[PDB]
Amino acid sequence: GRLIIVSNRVAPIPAAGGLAVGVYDALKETGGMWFGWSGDVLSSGQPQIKVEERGPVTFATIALMRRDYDQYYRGFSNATLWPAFHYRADLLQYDRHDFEGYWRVNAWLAQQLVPLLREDDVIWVHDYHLIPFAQALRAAGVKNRIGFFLHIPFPASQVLLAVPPHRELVEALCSFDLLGFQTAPDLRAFCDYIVNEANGTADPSASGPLTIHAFGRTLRAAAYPIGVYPDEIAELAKAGERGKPVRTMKATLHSRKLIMSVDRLDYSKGLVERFRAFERLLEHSTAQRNKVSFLQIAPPTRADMHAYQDIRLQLEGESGRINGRFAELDWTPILYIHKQYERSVLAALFRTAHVGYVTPLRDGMNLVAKEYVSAQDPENPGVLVLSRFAGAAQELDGALIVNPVDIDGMAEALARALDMPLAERQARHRDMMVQLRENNVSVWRDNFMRDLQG
Ligand SMILES: O=c1ccn([C@@H]2O[C@H](COP(=O)(O)OP(=O)(O)O)[C@@H](O)[C@H]2O)c(=O)[nH]1
Ligand SMILES: O=P(O)(O)OC[C@H]1O[C@H](O)[C@H](O)[C@@H](O)[C@@H]1O
């Protein structure tokens, strides 16, 4: 059967975002179709699907009308769902008219997909934009198997209650044949809502996935943590070891140690707290001054949204304060760059960084954490400092796990990472590489597809 991937964001045919990276890694091996938004917005006219073969993948993409982009994507998806599911009800905005457009765009996108389907296609929908998609497909006569994978956290039921149409969203989720979440706590939160807010049931099974009964429907649900190709990232990082970015980075640092971060400039990424803990490191450790620099690559994301403009402004003021307090004529403590980089360049740079600094307030998985570890030279690997609220913390035992709210704790982790002896750095890296290898992105895809077809 042909695998049909459905997502809002489709890989570029460099972009920051782990969905596009991970889905493309999975899809290029099996081949199939990738259907979704082209990334373009129309002021007038009519969107038209564009079908194009790129090796084993068929891309089927379509623009959004401005009104659809505003209501479905900027509106309900990123002004309601994204903040709510990342435990930011304070940033949640809700507009009934945007929620209706969100529902309408899902139905319109499903209508665009129907003519391309075949009887034995297997449909795999990805992420929070497309929660109503199975319901729309079924209403359009579609009988294929349909699975869903949520890339972002599934919030605690009490937090989900802040989304006014929470019940309609969860009922729509129950039209899927199979629901996949990143981690066990995500699945637990879903089941907690089903049992305690939807009057349904969630039962274990010998097969693996739970059986869900709710809203008159029966379906399955399980956790499938998205992974990477760790040995592929290692070879990529090694192949850049004599490239210009690594060579100029080395020259600029001239023997100073490097703390490195790579994050869309999203309020979910805890970047203000991250900067404050680097500042706290410098306040308390005079020996670290002029001996380390912090590279934060923070590409623009969703920049036409006030909330993203706000977090950008806050972070830029942080960099100015901290640099102003601690800089010397030959030392800039924080190297803040508000631009996207090629993933191949980031891998090469990860391999030169003594510390990978990944401290999101909430994160469904965080591929950057897995990429940082994968890039390391096993003869001399750096240390991952990792938020306990990143989904990757459930499996990456060799990281230094921190609570991003605890500024002192994060600064102490930075000091511990910078001074960690080789033997322990290697032991942690070795353990994590085993985990990443056994639970790579091919295994993830095979596991979900096995459950969806069974
Ligand atoms: O300039 C950049 C920044 C990030 N990324 C990639 O974007 C992904 C980010 O995924 P992650 O899970 O860390 O976070 P997200 O953006 O999905 O919240 C990773 O594969 C990064 O290598 C990239 O290609 N270029
Ligand atoms: O697609 P954007 O809005 O640019 O955000 C980039 C990506 O961020 C996260 O990874 C989301 O889980 C993806 O669904 C999204 O594609």
Image (tube, rainbow, N blue to C red):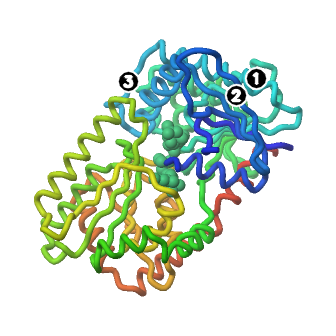
Tell me where residue 257 appears, x and y as whole percent. Answer: 30, 75
Q: Position of residue 367 (x, y in %)?
A: 51, 56
Q: Which residue is mark 1?
A: 138
186 shown above or below 44: below
Q: Nearer the viewer, residue 120 or 337?
A: 337
Amino acid identity at mark 3: Gln
Vertical placement of 114 versus 369: above or below? above
Nearer to us in this view, 429 or 221: 429
What secondary structure is marked by label 2?
Answer: helix
Q: Residues within 10 Å of mark 1 (few under 14, many from 20)?
A: some
Q: What x and y, as percent, mark residue 43?
A: 53, 18
**Structural distance between the alpha carbons of marks 3 and 2:** 25 Å
- Residue 190 higher or lower than 338, as above or below: above
* Residue 305, quarter of picture: top left
Give the amino acid at mark 2.
Ala
Determine which residue is flagged by label 2: 134
Secondary structure at numbered mark 1: helix
Query: As drawn, is 124 to the left or to the right of 288?
Result: right
Marks 3 & 2, CB-CB < 8 Å contact: no
Q: Name the outermost residue toward the top.
A: 97
Query: Does residue 189 show up?
Result: no
Q: Residue at x 79, y 35 (%)?
A: 145
Residue at x 12% of width, y 57% of height: 324
Residue at the limit of the structure toward the right, as seen here: 119
- Viewer can see residue 50: yes
Helix, strand or loop at disc 3?
loop
